[PDB]
Length: 308
Length: 308
Image (tube, rainbow over the protein chains, first blue to last red):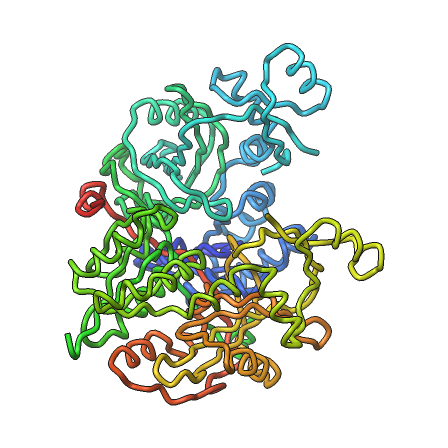
């Protein structure tokens, strides 16, 4: 409705706390969730939850378009990297049914998704980044020339492999929001990643650093990246290395939220056609986030009340 | 006090939900926490939390005894395997200051902690268990005789290594409580482990199975194991294999709690000198548990209000 957005959060998975934040901040309208598994905990943080195909299934987008029309969805957001480009590529189909896909442009999503293209972007822009190799020959050459040392990370190329320089330093997880109307960066939240758990930031400390703010602003300036964003950085002997740009909410976003940096409220305001006023660095440093498991119980019968 | 126990939970770590359960069920008295790191989330679920030495430091027990006397602690419980034997061995020192250590006897803790001695126990008792080898020669012999196949798990011996038969089947996490006064098993909660996350049960389904109840009862009968316990089992083609006995709360305990199987209340009752009435299998099957992260924020100044 005119005053009531209906946000569908797809690939909700385990991001229960994030969906809770959205439910709380959508003061009018509705927040619904979708995932391919009924065992995704985040599904049950919203009133309406739907089982959809897996993102790699051919009929995924066809199904989302039909779900959107049937359930009066006005906007769509994914929480996972592999779905970003898929939704970006399909934006015109969603626009043809009146649905706004909250995703950065396709080319930007794909540039960020492929670790090698991301590296090439950094080299062009003058942004520090771990030396990265897409072929075995170039890695051997680099070892031969002393350009890279013995200990190394071998990662998959997307998210074919890549080998890259082992960066030893303080890892930083930066949450950033680019206003969907004005195109300006409105908030940046920087945390030191202290402890990792199952590939996510489990413990962290908020920090205020002009260098990180300036680096992120410079990178976002003219990028075309919009909405909630995540930057992975490394402070290595006082120099900031860009490791990843993930055009979606970072797993450490709850730190930002609890410190007053509210992307779901800004997103809600943008769907209500309001521009958010930029307020960069208006949070407290030296605030620690410590994650811990809580639980949701659901009976098989209650689980069976959806499953298509 | 006579009506007021003071339970200290050591090595609280990340078990925030479990400490919350204890705070709720200790209707009189107090529940406090301890850990070696101020970044242990479970610390802040209790009113009084203390930083103690690491469990392997020589002065650990000396420090716990002094903390207990200074803070009027009446009972002590650990949440980690490596501390069980340490506290069991020191029980008389705690008894000399009037403190009840809630731990199974030392020999039992050590038999359960060492994977090889646990295997030998099973062989003696007729309990199915994965073929396990403490030497490289015996593993080669077993491969030579066709007693073990190509794919294998290599685990550390405690919690020197061991190699053992790769069990392929439905993994079961059984929570069990043995009454501290009567010595009888009062509750057994069985869940199928569906998904693992960082070595813990993340998703599970409650089940009612006579075979598991009987196996656990038979194992506990005359064992000397007391208080909260955790059994790791595998259903492999209809046969139950015993994988682990961990004489402490299992990581999937919140499933049991939320289904009405309340060990913290039973523990509280035992410290209030009440025997718990056995009520085995009085819960609903087909109830799924789905864990998800919540958060605790703490400032560095607030963190600094303890740290010894």
